[PDB]
Image 1 (spheres, rainbow, N blue to C red):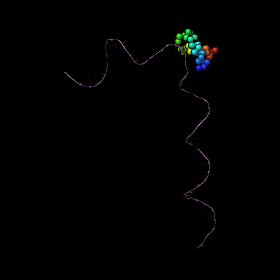
Image 2 (cartoon, rainbow, N blue to C red; image 1 turned 90 degrees about the vertical axis):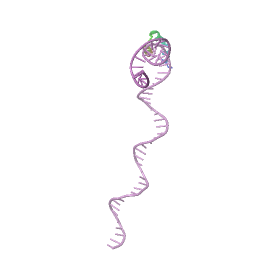
Image 3 (cartoon, rainbow, N blue to C red; image 1 turned 90 degrees about the horizontal axis):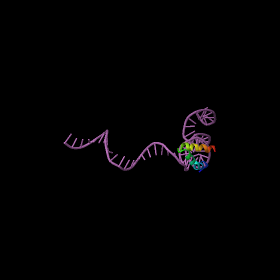
Length: 36
DNA sequence: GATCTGGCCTGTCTTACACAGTGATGCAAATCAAGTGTGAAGCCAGACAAAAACCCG
């Protein structure tokens, strides 16, 4: 486990509520994680 | 005529030299640690009908 893995496991429901479908969801997650 | 001597011939060590090994490093690269999230396949229950080869009348 790493910081990115923890952030993903913590904010996956965010992308879930945002878009159902997870290419674009994971892309946006990685983008916002690299931004923050 | 009787030895004395310089120059090849050739079987000798003798000696350097590259290679094969042992071990360990050490970077380039393929794969995986988990996160969902679909998304396309594989097979099975329900009962009903088409190609291909060998033997008999």
